[PDB]
Length: 298
Length: 296
Image 1: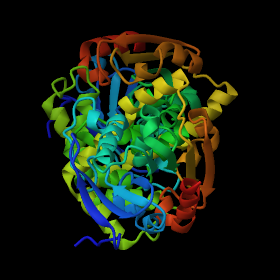
Image 2: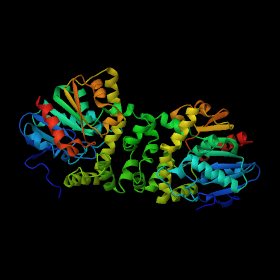
Image 3: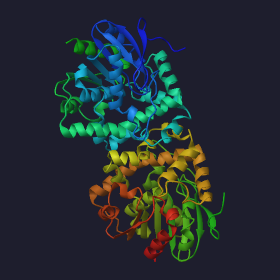
Image 4: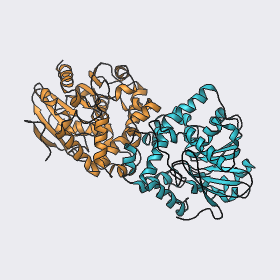
């Protein structure tokens, strides 16, 4: 009873070696892959992907393990939910469609996959936009009292299983709603289309989906940080022209000035704040869409 | 619920903020023992009888914990700040005629204890803190490693009712998880099952969990600000003090505890105990030994 929020978009179940990636696919022109983050699914793009689809073949995919994508079984190192792995799996998915070179915009966890993709396999990306993130390394390196309080869930969801899972399972609805709400500008759910919230809530209702989210966060604390650490200590920069968009009241701007940070990671980065909380494409769809269209159309 | 303090009486000590529950036994100089999170006074059940051979031992539930009353909190978590708990415990000791006493605290109770020593050092003959560094030091050393290790310092201090609602998701699991994961063994085998039942029952009460959260909210806000002012004015604890910490405890995950405490205390003695976080229960003999030696 989940709404179809991408009227006119097709649906694809893309097989990869790590499981099927679900995607809505619409538009035509150059391929643009949109990746959501937590605690969301591909439908968070539903307000901007139509605009995007006027100019691009828009592929709106659920991350590995999220939404209707399959859930690779994780391991002690949370390997399939490391951004490196997810990027490789999304690269595979895109190859299934014939897209070996594509534009990529990610938000939140999807943005982490995206900049990791761009570090690991920059030849896959024409351009990269990341929405309301700094690299995982930067969040962890900026993890002082103020920021540990702000993004407590980085520590909490990365606790060994089954601790987050057990607590999240008592009232999953509360938690997904709380995160959605608290990272918006308003502090409530009013930015979101209720039909979109239903998608998030239903995804969150599945204990396996929750586990995957924790795995994602577990990777975010461990391997993802390690991978980032290697690159930043090696001076490895993303060579792909990139856009860093962040919400003026989003999470990234709370750790540090986002463009300063990103210029350390990317040799060709432009940046813009958007008056918005974390959920740029739902809180600020027009502004987001326009920034992405302008960037990817250059 | 077992009586783990045979021969101790049980007193309800009135204060202006509510009743403090305490087991009291022994005779001789008063020694107040304060537990921490997520426990209650019975955490002292293995060490208290040895202390009671030489001291009047008051084994108190912190304000809001165990069987002590829960003062209503406020937007600043005032009653659950260590300053406010210290004040309430001083008042409770005064009700017993104890205006000058020895104090040992573990975890949250040790935070009350050193804040007590900073605020009202005339109240204390000697002080022992078990497996803590000052709250300021945990937050100042906040980084990736410590954020993951003491994630609950950020989690429990999130605004209500988020931790409350989460904790309510599986309270029996959480408290056993807290207890197990901070031990050397990594399971509950160091605890007396009857003590665990005490811990489980207190944590089963949502209002009790709320207070624990209020304590941690205090830990993140007011307690840190109070500590900062002492750091920034150079105030040191002038009370002879013993810092004990588990070789695999929380305190040493942040820094070398004795060198930390030397910054906070003029007269600090220190020793690592072969244990995780729950010194009196994992390492009852070594812990009691050190406390007796120190306080006598």
